[PDB]
Length: 5
Length: 7
Length: 425
Image (cartoon, rainbow over all chains, first blue to last red; front, side, top):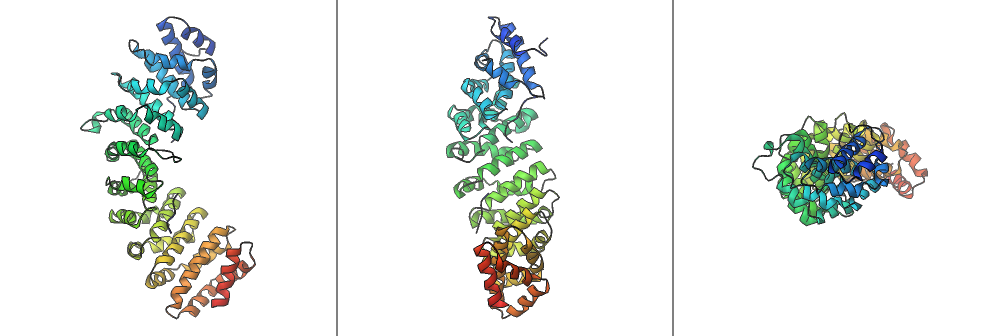
């Protein structure tokens, strides 16, 4: 899924 | 970015 | 006059009970501290001059001594954390906040600069500057109908100081402070100065790095079209924080991601993904991986903007860090994409550059590639074209690479590799 910094 | 000194 | 003085000479002049002698020794201190090589910051600190400078900040009847101590203290606060701490320990925060109300623009400005250096040290000094009430007087300086009436240098310093009040993560700035700053910051993001735009973008990049609630705060202020418009600038100092902020926004909800697409961000990515600066290419591919991790209609808009051959290219040749983001972009694409969307990826030549990255000495990228191959074989199972992809992987020497990964250190690499060979080869 989506990955932050 | 970070700190800035004058002259 | 006030050039090449010793610390003991400055101490003598500041310890006199003569304002003019104090003014000349303070000018001499500022000059010593302005010099490029090894200014004697620690020497001035050890001499006990910081409380003296801080007290001179309150000398309203002597505006030049206010300026000179302000400048001297600014350069001490621009040093190490212990050096910034010294200025704070000297009680300079309330003193500088009072100076923001000065009728002398150059003193008012020096106060803004010094508060920027203090807040920029970290979360604790940032929040201490906010607690002493710096935000209200700083925002009152920008309460003009047109930002263009203010001096360029003065406007640049305010924007940079405000960006440091938006900076640092454990914790993030107080929500109330972020809400009070945001209307001025949006107004600065539309100003016609390249340094004002860059620093405004940095501030937005800091606010969007964290929880989705904080991304929502920013996105609700309608800044996304302006960030996309700045994403296309010719100045690299503007594109770098603009892409950062857009990159952050797409780490949030699909709805937040959609706002970026609707503003037309994907049209800029053909250049972004071929940008000569590695960091831009790496960050663009990372931004791409978080978009391909979205809905099937979002993956479809990536396809529609002809961005799949651009991902094929970055995967084929780029910096290894950019190639690592590209593998992630493909695994995300193949995870949530339709059979038609995955088939289109193989047709664009994804198999060969994907197989060549299996020679890497990084276990994480190998794991990401093996998951992408598994997702491509599942789409091939649904069409009865498993043998077609099996020969396709064998032709470009893909199979050999997976054969060697059966005897690997990592268990997750060892399992997935042995599984594909017994299931399809």
